[PDB]
Amino acid sequence: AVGACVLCNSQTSLRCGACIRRPFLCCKCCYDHVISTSHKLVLSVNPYVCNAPGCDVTDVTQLYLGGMSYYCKSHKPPISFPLCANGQVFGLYKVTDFNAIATCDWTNAGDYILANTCTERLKLFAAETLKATEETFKLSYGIATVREVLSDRELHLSWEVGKPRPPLNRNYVFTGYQIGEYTFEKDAVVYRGTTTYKLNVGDYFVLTSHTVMPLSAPTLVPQEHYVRITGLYPTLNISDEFSSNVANYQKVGMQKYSTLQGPPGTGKSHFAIGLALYYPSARIVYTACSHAAVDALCEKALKYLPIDKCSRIIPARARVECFDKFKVNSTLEQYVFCTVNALPETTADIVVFDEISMATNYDLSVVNARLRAKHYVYIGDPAQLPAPRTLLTKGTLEPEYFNSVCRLMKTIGPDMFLGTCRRCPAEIVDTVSALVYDNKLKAHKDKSAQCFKMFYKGVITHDVSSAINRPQIGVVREFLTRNPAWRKAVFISPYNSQNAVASKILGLPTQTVDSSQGSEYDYVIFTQTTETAHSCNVNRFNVAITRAKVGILCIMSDRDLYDKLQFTSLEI
Ligand SMILES: O=C(c1c(F)cccc1F)N1CCCC1
Ligand SMILES: [Zn+2]
Ligand SMILES: [Zn+2]
Ligand SMILES: [Zn+2]
Image (cartoon, rainbow, N blue to C red):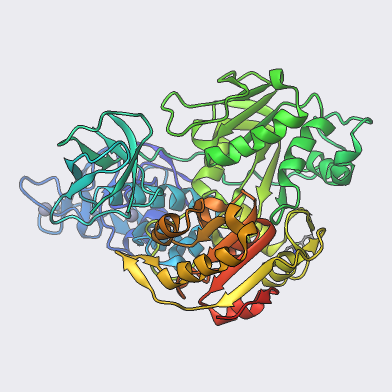
């Protein structure tokens, strides 16, 4: 009931009852809120309400203190003070940006912009508020009751009338009823049970809204610069493999936190694991939002670090198949590999947070909450894809607003930049270097002469809102008969519905751009499918074409992105 003010930390009794988080506001700040917003309910030990029987006045602006009790204009005794006076709300121990965060629906980009340009305590308020709002939106969607079970990977669904139907991608993970988590793909719908169960007809699925805990720790701890490497002990015997990263590794030990911008295939995993070999006695917690990113760091560790000193931390509510080659759930091992949501309460000499473009400010805070560390390293690329903002439908979120780390990387620049792409044919490196990396990304590989582009708008059909371009899949089919080396190629598009069609016609393994991020394939076929802001997003485009080691075919809808591709153009 008595806590600290989210804007000035000033001790107070006052909480906003109208805010969904109910933040402590100090007399001077609580006023500026309630006088400028539809937010009028204030809480103390007891609510600021008229205490007269049957009186429904709760608006703090229309209330008075009569003794130790509160009354409206109609019930106040002659000797009474207005609760709102001289820029204050009467409480014990006697902001434009707070108001916008407190009252926005989170459907506008500008909401996310403000949640990242504001002060540090307002980043936490925003991050809880947003996440709270995201969770209570899941309740808006209708229940899926099973009408008929066709097979072990297909069934038919009956949807709740009067409630919208959630996108049936892999993004939207349902909870079945507790028959385990389930996902769906597009009357024949494809079902995938994290726990395998003889699917019972009549059983139902619901999206698991998880309670949003409060944030305490900042997104980013305060920066500390040191004169010598602090708390870490370097080798003099670091293998030439990692000699390229020694100067950056010393920067890591002479700062509290450091930022690494690593474009695709520039040696991020190599950097992260090489840090353990440079500071060989240091305890390092390796974290990322997704299981795939933490498992990617496990593969690299398996190759270079002693397997006995590694532990993969798996939450007992296991949702996807996870890295198996380490001892599982040994929190005390020198090397700990854990998703942000599973992190234990522990300490560490270095924390490495990977895939930083995918992190929210909520995730940045949780990490700082669960891990007390001498050094924090943030690895990723603001030119790659951010975490999906399910509520955002109006305006595009720029990379400087993805989170606090990406905002630093886009304004004052990253502390360290890996500038040489060792994965991609020069045609792809040249294209993305000019598009998102200000001509600072360099190609280690030669031109493959296997990078082709074709301008072909085709015809755009929709499965609800997910896009399909059959003629673009048709052009790929034609190309494959003539280019049989591409039979091994991964098919990539910005839409699962296009991928679903391309899976039946082509038989290629299928991937969305967003699910492709962090993976590489010798050959990539990309159909842009549509000209929308989704399919023309330069970050998504960057990730799409930088998956390829040897060749790429890009069937394009957007003239701009087609022209920019420094690829050999095809006809038809
Ligand atoms: O100009 C740079 C840069 C660099 F070239 C070296 C170090 C830090 C930097 F921000 N970049 C633009 C986007 C990709 C990196
Ligand atoms: Zn409020
Ligand atoms: Zn205050
Ligand atoms: Zn009253």
